[PDB]
Amino acid sequence: GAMGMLKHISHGDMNAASDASVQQVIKGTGIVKDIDMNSKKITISHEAIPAVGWPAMTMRFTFVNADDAINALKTGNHVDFSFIQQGNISLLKSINVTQS
Ligand SMILES: [Ag+]
């Protein structure tokens, strides 16, 4: 059949929102340096993240649930991630592999 559904392809009609569950979810980047699903800690050598105000250091991030991203995640991989600060505990919400 002739499938030609005239939708707003014109990127300017903002009907969809990029936000949903962003409660100041602090985003950053760095190279994964270790993954421990057992204690749910992922030690990532992370860069200067100005959103939290932390310099380029190696530190572990606690995740709530092992996602498909976290499953396909490997050490040595340069990634961009998103977490929320909880005292000293950096609670990893989501993680994106940008360079493997
Ligand atoms: Ag740190």
Image (cartoon, helix red, strand yellow):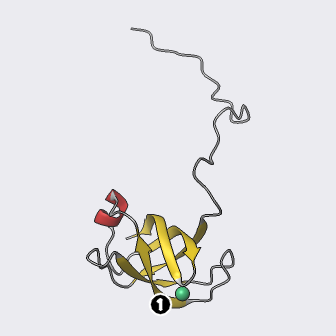
Could you tell me which residue is drawn at 72 percent across and 31 percent down? Answer: 13
Of all residues, the one furthest to the left in this rendering is 38
- Of residues 43 and 65, which is closer to you in this image? 65
- Eyeballing the image, is 11 above or below 32? above
- Of residues 53 and 28, which is closer to you in this image? 53
Tell me residue 20's x, y (percent).
59, 47
Q: Name the quadrant containing residue 47.
A: bottom right
Ligand 1 is found in the corner quadrant, namely bottom right
- Eyeballing the image, is 12 above or below 71? above
Could you tell me which residue is drawn at 54 percent across and 75 percent down? Answer: 29
Tell me residue 24's x, y (percent).
65, 63
- Eyeballing the image, is 73 above or below 32? above
In the figure, is residue 12 to the left or right of 18?
right
Tell me residue 99's x, y (percent).
43, 70
Could you tell me which residue is drawn at 57 percent across and 81 percent down? Answer: 87
Quadrant in the picture for the C terminus: bottom left
Which secondary structure lies at badge 1?
Answer: strand
Q: Amino acid at mark 1?
A: Thr
Residue position marked by numbered label 1 in the rendering: 58
Cβ(mark 1) to ligand 1 < 8 Å?
Answer: yes
- Eyeballing the image, is 56 above or below 14? below
In the figure, is residue 22 to the left or right of 96?
right
Of all residues, the one furthest to the front in this rendering is 87
